Image (cartoon, rainbow over all chains, first blue to last red; front, side, top):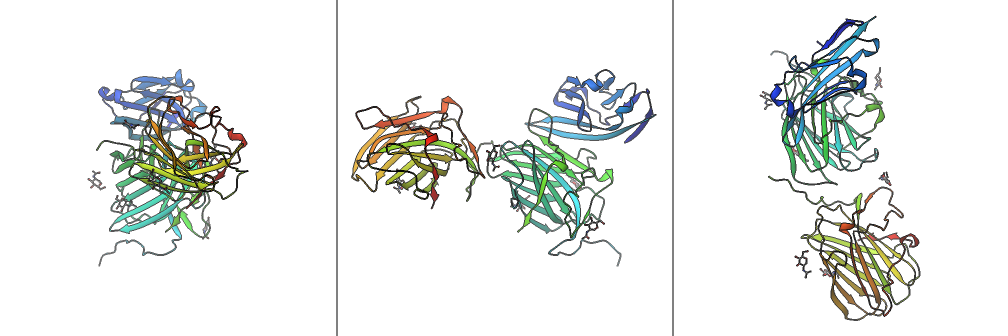
Length: 106
Length: 203
Length: 203
């Protein structure tokens, strides 16, 4: 679902669209970003959420590496991209890229 | 006697360009700014294979598209911050809507020269319907990013005066390949509007 | 198929210079000041040996680095006080952190010519991990001092406009060889910021 539209204050769900077994998360880095403003990082099990989204961000690995933002705000409208990288021998290889756009009606 | 589209004949000056792909290479030696006349390019459409070789800024880039009706017509190079090199590639029009396998070979010629440091296959991230055979000869590259059929990128910058320029607008034709050799994130992105580009010289 | 660094391919005009060494030679005949076009240089990377021959100011200097992955790319000469001649040598980048044996032959061409006045092996003073085979044909040299991988010396002086210049910052790679033929102290030092250097012409 490239385009998702939710009303203000509702629950926003964005699916990275890729399923990764819990076994390989150590050899995987997952980045959710929004127009080159980092949102969430899962570097080899070490997580990190930026201040703009630390309070209202839930990351679900099982559900297609999806994220949930509660209490949608008018300034959160934009395009979000999910990138998954696998640690191959002496390199980090991008194994999936997904782009999703969220619009807020007010 | 059934109709089928075919590639346009060769010429000397192609006035119709298509934004085929965008390549950003990050290097661990110093490149300062764009230099006029630095880049030199050669091209060949043999069989249904298209091949471009570019020399400049201490790198040789050999890019091939496999089983294609396109032909390479132009390339431009530019340099941005943090030793980033951007290569814009322009082919003839795209006839069929099918992803093609790519082969990229990057060789270092001025700094950190060596033998084959990397050789692998990169899946197409968005659709997983193609692949890029990446080969790197040297210890000079830190990241490679390949965008086939760019959409967001605006190739009009210094739009050449006498030519026509076309760009993809569908999200289903996008393709994104990439590898990063550094512990940090890929960070192989760079803004197009902050790069000063120069057309490569055919020879 | 194990990766190993290799020397960069030859070119016509190099742009990435490395401050290989500094050589100071004091003479007992008169030299006034620098002359634009006095020095002429020749270079050869044969086997793993690098060789440079410089002709100017009444001297011929034949310097050789043995079993190295470097190549000589440039040299500059300048005339200081009390008939002191300074030679700045620039090679390609350094790959391994190993001290290389050096050979230096100084021949007089205009004053105090002769046969082989000196032939000896100077130890590396700081670390004693290399040696310099010094040969002197003539009676014109009072002192000689070779500084390999200088740190304190600043090679930026008239930094060439279109090049890049690198230098060693580690004390562990410094090397200092020297011989004085006069009853006084070596006194072969000369300040860099008081010598009007000029680039030797390749031929």
